Image (cartoon, rainbow, N blue to C red; front, side):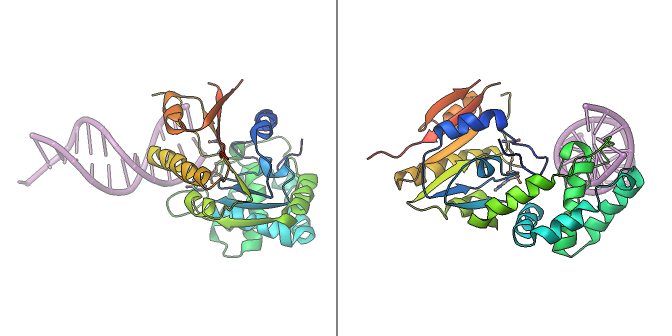
Length: 246
DNA sequence: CTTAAACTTAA
DNA sequence: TTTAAGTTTAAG
Ligand SMILES: Nc1ncnc2c1ncn2[C@@H]1O[C@H](CSCC[C@H](N)C(=O)O)[C@@H](O)[C@H]1O
């Protein structure tokens, strides 16, 4: 399996084989919650539409795509032993938050992802990244993963927008895979948004556009995805397949 | 995960 | 004429 170059939630390498098992074939894959892009990186659609509400993420992806060698050379300079200390980390974090240059921000974003606590991406309400130092022994520089991402990205378009807007880009030749923020385990991304996502999926499948949604397997998700074909993986993971008729 | 700060609420 | 209690946010 191909690895994402970012530490990120939703890395589903165990679930990847299961996702692909239920992901229909098509010309184009639409991912409204692309995240680290594990599915994009491990499928073979002719083209991709990849979206996320995180603007730093989407900016980074197009920079890696379009300015690959330049980016790798710049980012690699930050993965040295001298940068692995709290004082340096918090200054790079400040530089990131004060920068208005997309390229420099994208370079620092990778450093912060690998040197910060548990690959978290957390902002305050003013849009400032505020994840603390991770105190790792030796962070890994994902050079190979970066180049593989860039190569695959030649057939992808990236959009910073919410799920409703990106799902509207789907057409008859599209397949849609949704990996929303997880629903609550026991009985931000709101419950209303969770239900709304399902409503959009129902609209798409009526237009003969297949939609696959992954989430926790709870009574609430089963109610949301009640019009889909439900598959349980291995709290368990739920795969909701909206499969068009004939 | 935790504590602290910011901010609102109620009587 | 006030402030303990709640709720949300910040950040190590
Ligand atoms: N309203 C929205 N529209 C599109 N993307 C969104 C969104 N809200 C959050 N996201 C993105 O969705 C991605 C989820 S990755 C999360 C995967 C997994 N279900 C988990 O919860 O851990 C994140 O990258 C986040 O930036």
